[PDB]
Length: 10
Length: 10
Length: 240
Length: 237
Ligand SMILES: CC(=C(c1ccc(O)cc1)c1ccc(O)cc1)c1cccc(Nc2ccccc2)c1
Ligand SMILES: CC(=C(c1ccc(O)cc1)c1ccc(O)cc1)c1cccc(Nc2ccccc2)c1
Image (tube, rainbow over all chains, first blue to last red):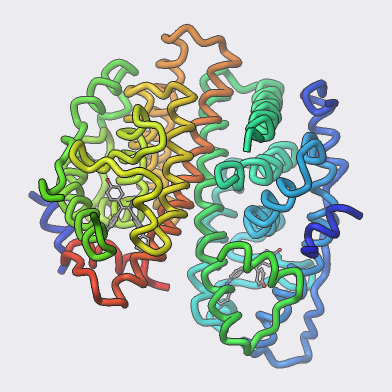
């Protein structure tokens, strides 16, 4: 849910 | 001035 | 896991190739400086740097072997340290000045425009002078930056453990790389371990600057006068 | 000109070992409240500080610095030094922090003071790390000396002297590792491992210093004039 989390996924 | 001064000098 | 199978030279090449670009600020030299704009320039710059950093981190050997939650933690802990060592590196050849961006070169007097900034500026400059004196090499710099990424948050992490273990294996790998570089530079064994120590001890000061910097950011945040980006906010909250 | 630079590794080790401060005791009365625990920890630290100065004057090379440079280093590193000492004492007590022989605290007692739990956990992690590394007394005294000389060196020839002495201590650490039978690779890897932990100790000190600021503003826990002066050295900004 966190932005960092999301960006680390992509 | 500073207690630290005295401790160092002694 | 490749990472552990990399030769020293392959580690270095991998790290060099993954280097983020040097970004520009929005600095409009026609615009009169205010504490709100200078801080705005810095935050805007840092915000865009963060996106590159995140993608740089994925290219650091071993990093993507970690669970995602570990990846998140490491970056939450190290982001400012990494921005700072980058800034200090960029500023090596500009004695008395900090090259935040090619179009944003600030000296000490200009840090005064933001209360409490001057101390931070002085600490960053001192670190830059330190690198200059040691004649820090680009190869050594990228090793140091990778070490920060893997090390800063490693002691604030059940049964998991094996995550900690792998991280330390990679860290040791990077140590092997630094020594390999120094040996090739012609340094004696005594010199090698002295320089290794000198380099890693600087990491203590970088941690210190990050901590203090975070303290000011966390405060001016509540002051609301200067807006942080959504990414920086979540990064900042992670330290509280 | 100094003196510390002429020492051999063995002489450096013996000098540091001999300079070691004593293990102090806490008050002999027992269920802590927030005021009680902070009182004990503060009184203890205050007493330890006096001995730290004695120890500092006996760290080779430290006496060669001007009074002001000595003051700067101690003001910068005093909490790091207390913490690495605390961590070292706790090594043999997994899950516990040995503040004093009569003051051994587990993680749970950290919850007494608000925000102490996080600090406790970090300290315990460091102690566990040292234990798993099998840190030796001879290595510990080198690390502690390094903190004293390193932490404030960039907040300042004198810097050269300090950096020359730090090199001397590095030489000493490597010597100890080579003596324990470590290969050259193991020596470098171990040196790095120990030095990286110094980064965490700095982090704990800063986090710790932050709370001490606020606890001072709370004005519920008395702080000795000495600690206040040591504290105020950081309390800007
Ligand atoms: C150097 C630096 C920053 C910085 C460092 C390296 C960069 O490449 C890009 C940016 C920074 C980072 C994020 C921000 O939102 C703003 C600046 C920094 C970091 C924290 C604090 C301070 N000083 C300060 C002093 C008083 C009040 C607020 C901040 C500076
Ligand atoms: C461990 C530790 C302290 C400590 C560490 C090692 C010692 O041998 C002796 C003493 C300490 C030092 C000075 C004091 O006046 C009180 C305690 C410490 C330092 C700073 C902060 C904290 N935690 C904390 C959390 C919330 C509010 C106030 C403090 C602990």
